Length: 148
Ligand code: HEM
Ligand SMILES: [Kr]
Ligand SMILES: [Kr]
Ligand SMILES: [Kr]
Ligand SMILES: [Kr]
Ligand SMILES: [Kr]
Ligand SMILES: [Kr]
Ligand SMILES: [Kr]
Ligand SMILES: [Kr]
Ligand SMILES: [Kr]
Ligand SMILES: [Kr]
Ligand SMILES: [Kr]
Ligand SMILES: [Kr]
Ligand SMILES: [Kr]
Ligand SMILES: [Kr]
Figure 1: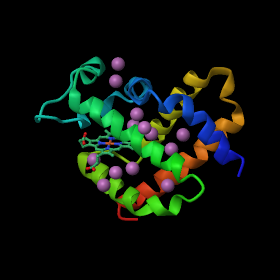
Figure 2: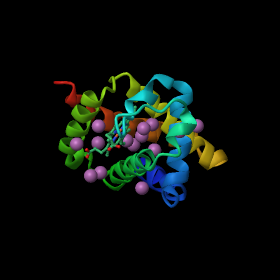
Figure 3: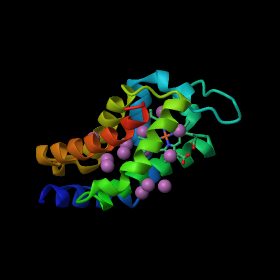
């Protein structure tokens, strides 16, 4: 496809500073849905405020984990079927930690936000539509983790 090249080219500039960019994604996320904050229980403790998460090594490690999973999607953009199995698993895990399926829509908007802000004039509506499709496919696979 040509959309596959839109994803690859758009990902390049972001992927080289994954923590800085994933920090924008999570900051947006908590701004849209603050009820996600408590889902991150390290040492059984809850973050009071969004800025509390950004001082947590474990939370920042999770940022990196996310950016890695996106990087895998980008890699396999032409053939997403290879990640299905892993993603179904990742969904069940998130079911178990307490994430509701509906929160993945917020996540996706947060991803689109972060790309928009990074790319500026380069984040064309085709680029947006390309990412929305890819994220779509990711969440489809992950939502098999809520039984079916
Ligand atoms: C509402 C959004 C999310 C919440 C509340 C959440 C929360 C968590 C928690 C609590 C863990 C276990 C603790 C940890 O390893 O840090 C976890 C693990 C993980 N999450 Fe998320 N997460 C979310 C979204 C995502 C997204 C969108 C991805 C990937 C694109 C992702 C990838 C991961 C990975 C890769 C792990 C490690 C799983 C394992 O191997 O056990 N998470 N997440
Ligand atoms: Kr992220
Ligand atoms: Kr954050
Ligand atoms: Kr924040
Ligand atoms: Kr990454
Ligand atoms: Kr991955
Ligand atoms: Kr992985
Ligand atoms: Kr993702
Ligand atoms: Kr998983
Ligand atoms: Kr999880
Ligand atoms: Kr996320
Ligand atoms: Kr994401
Ligand atoms: Kr997206
Ligand atoms: Kr994605
Ligand atoms: Kr996928």
